Image (cartoon, grey):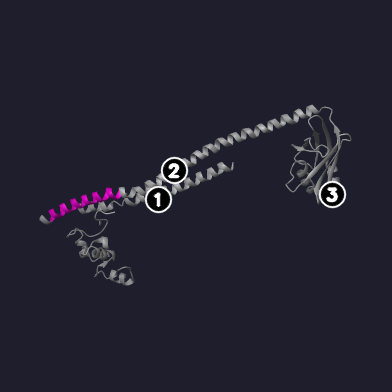
Amino acid sequence: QKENERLLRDWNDVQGRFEKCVSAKEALETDLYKRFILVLNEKKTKIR
Amino acid sequence: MERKISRIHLVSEPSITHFLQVSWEKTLESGFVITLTDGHSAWTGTVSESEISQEADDMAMEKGKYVGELRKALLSGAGPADVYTFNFSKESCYFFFEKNLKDVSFRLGSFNLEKVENPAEVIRELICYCLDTIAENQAKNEHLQKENERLLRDWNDVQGRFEKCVSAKEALETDLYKRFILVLNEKKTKIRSLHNKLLNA
Amino acid sequence: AGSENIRVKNIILSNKHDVVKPAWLLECFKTKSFVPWQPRFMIHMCPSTKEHFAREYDCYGDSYFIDTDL
């Protein structure tokens, strides 16, 4: 009983740090694309 | 309904393990039936609530505290500092049981007993019960093992994967920036093209 | 300016001057050569720099400046 409850709370804490890592990942994603490439789309307005 | 059986040794029989069985309804104070045996013969007695009141009020004690003591003594609730001792004469069918402190004994209580005419029958009953009890814990332990297995697998899996994910997260950005900076040069190419065309015309 | 002050702001508020971040001159010094300036190196500037922003005479704002670095 003690052993597997320990297994479980590591399991869950790993889930949590997984999600925080994922969230950092998502932030980095957005930071550069969705309208950060406006550095290009306004190179496109310069082209116009 | 509570039953509790206890392996004991009478002082009269150091080499014989005697077995103290207790049956009672959640509460030893209300009264109980007691059975003793040694594998060839068995005995039974009975005690009532008022007997315990009388015992506890001759203990100079609050009833209930003496009941906790009884839980320690007869239901094996005794601790390491607890040294109870049991005495019974099969000839007189008189039991009593005591407590050892100050290098001395203190008779806690004492019961009128009687030899049972059917030792083997109470024996079958007790031990069938015990078999059942064994078996239950066995099955429980089995299941517990199974889920211990499952969790130990899952923990390793998720740990390795989380590490790999952290690795890729650190890997991503340079991929992205190489991918850009070339396109950014290329649009700078198109820019310089149209700009030189504008200066020419 | 290594760091701002309200005088920075003043000369920021007085755009008659072009206000420069420190590392680029170190860059120029480490280049042993004047590296010509662009928004890589600045905080804020009079518009004449901005008409320069082609590395020549034809734009005005930002959401643009980078030379293919990381």
Occupied quadrant, residue B139: top right
In the image, taking residue B165 as reference, residue A41 lies left or right, namely left
| Residue B73 visible in the shown view | yes
Q: Height in image: B145 above or below A37?
A: above
Occupied quadrant, residue C12: bottom left
Q: Position of residue B36 (x, y in %)?
A: 80, 34
In the image, taking residue A18 as reference, residue B111 lies left or right, namely right
Residue type at mark 3: give it. Met
Residue that carries the numbered disc 2 in the rendered image: B160
In the image, taking residue C39 as reference, residue B84 lies left or right, namely right
Residue that carries the numbered disc 1 in the rendered image: A24
Element class at badge 2: helix
Residue type at mark 1: give it. Ala
Give the foreground label among 1 and 3. Answer: 3
Element class at badge 3: loop
State the extent of the magenta-drawn residues as a range. Answer: B176-198
Q: Which mark is residue B59?
A: 3
Give the foreground label among 2 and 3. Answer: 2
Q: Height in image: C49 above or below B11?
A: below
Residue count near mark 1 (Cα–Cα under 10 Å), binned few <14, some 14–19, many ≥20: few
Q: Position of residue A23 (x, y in %)?
A: 41, 49
